[PDB]
Length: 114
Length: 114
Length: 114
Length: 114
Ligand SMILES: CC(=O)N[C@H]1[C@H](O[C@H]2[C@@H](O)[C@@H](CO)O[C@@H](O[C@H]3[C@H](O[C@@H]4O[C@@H](C)[C@@H](O)[C@@H](O)[C@@H]4O)[C@@H](O)[C@H](O)O[C@@H]3CO)[C@@H]2O)O[C@H](CO)[C@@H](O[C@@H]2O[C@H](CO)[C@H](O)[C@H](O)[C@H]2O)[C@@H]1O
Ligand SMILES: CC(=O)N[C@H]1[C@H](O[C@H]2[C@@H](O)[C@@H](CO)O[C@@H](O[C@H]3[C@H](O[C@@H]4O[C@@H](C)[C@@H](O)[C@@H](O)[C@@H]4O)[C@@H](O)[C@H](O)O[C@@H]3CO)[C@@H]2O)O[C@H](CO)[C@@H](O[C@@H]2O[C@H](CO)[C@H](O)[C@H](O)[C@H]2O)[C@@H]1O
Ligand SMILES: CC(=O)N[C@H]1[C@H](O[C@H]2[C@@H](O)[C@@H](CO)O[C@@H](O[C@H]3[C@H](O[C@@H]4O[C@@H](C)[C@@H](O)[C@@H](O)[C@@H]4O)[C@@H](O)[C@H](O)O[C@@H]3CO)[C@@H]2O)O[C@H](CO)[C@@H](O)[C@@H]1O
Ligand SMILES: C[C@@H]1O[C@@H](O[C@@H]2[C@@H](O)[C@H](O)O[C@H](CO)[C@H]2O[C@@H]2O[C@H](CO)[C@H](O)[C@H](O)[C@H]2O)[C@@H](O)[C@H](O)[C@@H]1O
Ligand SMILES: [Ca+2]
Ligand SMILES: [Ca+2]
Ligand SMILES: [Ca+2]
Ligand SMILES: [Ca+2]
Ligand SMILES: [Ca+2]
Ligand SMILES: [Ca+2]
Ligand SMILES: [Ca+2]
Ligand SMILES: [Ca+2]
Image (cartoon, helix red, strand yellow):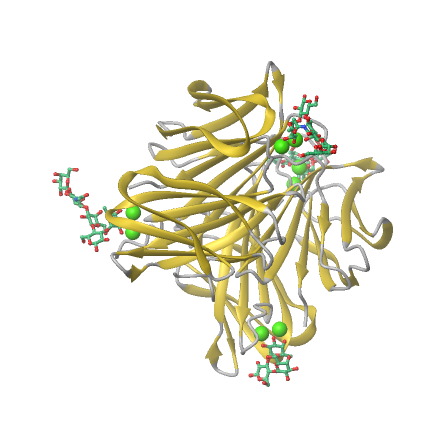
């Protein structure tokens, strides 16, 4: 199935934060309405934050996360979970290698903000 | 129900990260096997990452998150989600006020690392 | 925090299924737009299905699950999970006793159908 | 990523329930320790419960869901959710066609029971 694609409410600010757990430099691209809105880059094996930003979901609300490492797209796993009918998490894990730990870049999207 | 309590695998490193979305200064306490292991604080209405840390779950794997604002416990919501039977997120929201956005402090725990 | 309340897309059919795991007879009510839409009751300690129905979320999309045992409201815990940005689960557990298993009535809502 | 594979606690009873939403007849197989322990088949476009069963995770705890339509495997999506650190849902959707609704067979596993 497609992974890393989420429909947010329109015109809504959301947070996006990425963590790295890999020897490879992770490049995380966040696309809003099909256009690149943020790009994070970094390397850690200790869950460092490699980027955080606040974005607006725009007219459609479409948000897509993509991850690549040494020019190759990582395999993604994702889900959205909603707590108390209010608090939304869009979660992505990614795998750049052969161990299927799926933590190589971890991306958390959360809304609402404020 | 009790919220903000998670059983992790024993002797496992995990990340804990907190975000703020409130006019009130948030204080986030992270307990591991019933003793404080990390404390984060800050004040933002734009999702600032007020703290992030790597901890070890220790022998019994018990991790608890508590949130307070001006000495008053916040009401918590939480859940754990597991992707591809590998990648774990323990999620907490909290409410310090009257609007029930539950984002006033948001805490994300992730494992495994590395 | 409020539990067992979910906002569905309007005019959408959804399934609701309830299971029992308790010595007490479980009464499960499903409200749509603040009005009773379905009621199930039964008793099992081995996960029997005590009710299943297809409902329409109607003009409001507002769905609430309530659980009680002989006039005593059970404590609920709930969350919504979305897979591949398409497949939705609204999940409820409930506790009628002292063991905090939260399985005494379990309610699963899923959409879309068809 | 692998989907539909879950690690349960050993020697633990769990419920498994399957729903259908497709013109095609769904075949759902639930494997415990790599052998089929339950099978359900049926056709519905209205979320029929094509089967429910209580199984034991046995000595290994590995549980796998497979879905096919006249022998053709369906693509799966899955996740596990844990509420109040005690109530577990393992969730599966599947796609047999071209519309990406992922509801063609839906499988929910819950534990603990009793
Ligand atoms: C009927 C039965 O199962 N008897 C068991 C006894 O079971 C208890 C135990 O399950 C407790 C857990 O809190 O709950 C008692 O029931 C209370 C109700 O709880 C609900 O139903 C339960 C069955 C659980 O599903 C629970 O999660 C639910 O919340 C509650 O709603 C109600 O208001 O009050 C009830 C109590 O009045 C339930 O009776 O457990 C004992 C100890 O395990 C069993 O005794 C043991 O039996 C084994 C054989 O299996 C053996 O004989 C052993 O020596 C003996 O101690 C008893 O059979
Ligand atoms: C039988 C039926 O429902 N006929 C409908 C027609 O429905 C389509 C549509 O649902 C597509 C979606 O991809 O799938 C067709 O079935 C395919 C199988 O898909 C599975 O079953 C489906 C019912 C869905 O659940 C889907 O999610 C499943 O994956 C697939 O497994 C198989 O390999 O191939 C199948 C054929 O492609 C299904 O037939 O939809 C049309 C258009 O909406 C309906 O026609 C409209 O009917 C209304 C009245 O309701 C009115 O008459 C209107 O004018 C007319 O266009 C048709 O009745
Ligand atoms: C003074 C100001 O900025 N006014 C804008 C107003 O802001 C409100 C509104 O957000 C309400 C929502 O309940 O909360 C008030 O703040 C609370 C505070 O709530 C916390 O902080 C908020 C910013 C928000 O994040 C809440 O979710 C959070 O719980 C409480 O903690 C505190 O005890 O009491 C204060 C005061 O009541 C905000 O001041 O929002 C509107 C709507 O956008 C704007 O028009 C105002 O300019
Ligand atoms: C540290 C390690 O990084 C990543 O794996 C890399 C991979 O991206 C790259 O292409 O190739 C190397 C060498 O094989 C990988 O590193 C090894 O990964 C092993 C596990 O598969 C093991 O961790 C070795 O210690 C590494 O040298 C990640 O995909 C991996 O999860 C892990 O974080
Ligand atoms: Ca990896
Ligand atoms: Ca890794
Ligand atoms: Ca608030
Ligand atoms: Ca807030
Ligand atoms: Ca109970
Ligand atoms: Ca019970
Ligand atoms: Ca389909
Ligand atoms: Ca379908």
